[PDB]
Amino acid sequence: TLNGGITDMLTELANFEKNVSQAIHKYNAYRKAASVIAKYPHKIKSGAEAKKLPGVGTKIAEKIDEFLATGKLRKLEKIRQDDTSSSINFLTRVSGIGPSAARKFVDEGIKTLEDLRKNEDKLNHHQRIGLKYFGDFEKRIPREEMLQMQDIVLNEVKKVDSEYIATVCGSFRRGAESSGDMDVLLTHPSFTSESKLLHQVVEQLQKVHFITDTLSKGETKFMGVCQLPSKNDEYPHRRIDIRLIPKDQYYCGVLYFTGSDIFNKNMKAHALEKGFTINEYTIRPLAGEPLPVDSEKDIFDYIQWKYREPKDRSE
DNA sequence: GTCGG
DNA sequence: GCTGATGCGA
DNA sequence: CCGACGTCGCATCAGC
Ligand SMILES: Nc1ccn([C@H]2C[C@H](O)[C@@H](COP(=O)(O)C(F)(F)P(=O)(O)OP(=O)(O)O)O2)c(=O)n1
Ligand SMILES: [Mn+2]
Ligand SMILES: [Mn+2]
Ligand SMILES: [Mn+2]
Ligand SMILES: [Mn+2]
Ligand SMILES: [Mn+2]
Ligand SMILES: [Mn+2]
Ligand SMILES: [Mn+2]
Ligand code: NA
Ligand code: NA
């Protein structure tokens, strides 16, 4: 909260660059600045004090000066009051509608929720589901329900095969008081690098009516919707993602999947330096051959990082 | 947009 | 009908 | 000054 004004404004600029300008790297830049500034222990008194930090350059420094002087930002008010831009930004809030479809809808007059309803015919399945649950998906999931979902998912998985192991990862694993969704890392002895496991887990979860809709399904990833059962006399629908990972790659998998997204980018970068390439599966030398992983701490050892706990990788 | 080369 | 590239998201 | 900037899985539809 300490520097929320700045970071909120950077995050908003980041989103504009992604959704409207379709400039992914500028998106990345603002998010980096925002991340660095959120890790800064002091209260930012000037743009130049900000500019000392890596990721914060000339332009952002100016935008910080204006923000601390005016309380607002000229560039954003423009964006906010601009019909197209404000419209594109709103539409991308629908799961399945990104910068390109949003802009295409808008160019053809489809610019509000109603318009999407008026035009269901023009939405793919995933978009239709994002529409259907637009409200629910924007809600947070308080840890107490996360644990309630955790319990139901491990249980149903056991029921399929006692040798499954499911680790809920994502912000839950970082110990967050609320998460955006449920991310589930799944492994099984039958399946390794050398070696329908996912379909069976999904099918079972569909049968007890936990999973209610499918966004995408493959041999290793399921993206769908779920919902805790309530008193017979309704919980909001939630996004759940299940990843099937080869057992001997669990620790890389769970590193990736625990995040944060920025942690992962800061790690893969700060390992790209040291001659490693970290993906959700392996860690290779600069390239290359998959080194022995045996713990998460194992990955950190390699790239020379003081092992950070999950609750500390939220950047 | 930022920064190392 | 098929499929790469484009899109969207983890 | 310029251009590189993490790394993946699944679905969709143009252009044939
Ligand atoms: N661009 C990305 C996005 C995600 N992830 C990895 C790292 C993430 O930990 C993991 C899940 O991403 P998520 O889409 O469920 C998330 F990010 F929103 P989460 O971290 O879980 O916070 P919450 O969902 O509660 O809002 O995928 C990544 O490596 N790169
Ligand atoms: Mn200091
Ligand atoms: Mn998540
Ligand atoms: Mn997720
Ligand atoms: Mn060991
Ligand atoms: Mn294809
Ligand atoms: Mn340039
Ligand atoms: Mn056609
Ligand atoms: Na979207
Ligand atoms: Na420089």
Image (tube, coloured by chain):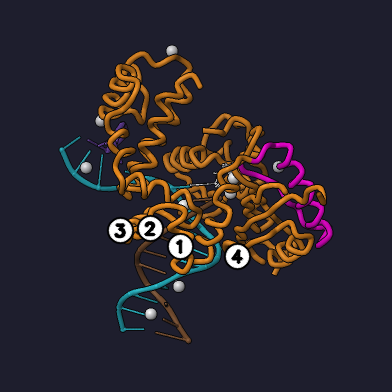
Chain colours: A orange, B purple, C brown, D cyan
Which residue bears the numbered disc 1? A118
Residue A107's tag is 3
Image depth: mark 2 or mark 4 in front: 2
Q: Which amino acid type is shown beneath numbered disc 3? A: Asp
- Which of the marked residues, 2 or 4, is nearer the chain's N terminus? 2
Residue A110's tag is 2
- Which of the marked residues, 4 or 3, is nearer the chain's N terminus? 3
Q: Residue at x 47, y 25 (%)?
A: A38
Mark 3, Cα crowd under 10 Å, few <14 / some 14-19 / many 20+, is: few
Both on one chain, marks 1 and 3?
A: yes
Mark 4, Cα crowd under 10 Å, few <14 / some 14-19 / many 20+, is: some
x, y (%) of residue A127? Answer: 50, 60
Specify whether A280 is left or right of A111. right
Mark 1, Cα crowd under 10 Å, few <14 / some 14-19 / many 20+, is: few
1 and 2 marks in contact (CB < 8 Å): yes
The range drawn in magenta is A141-170
* Closest to the observer, A90 or A281: A90
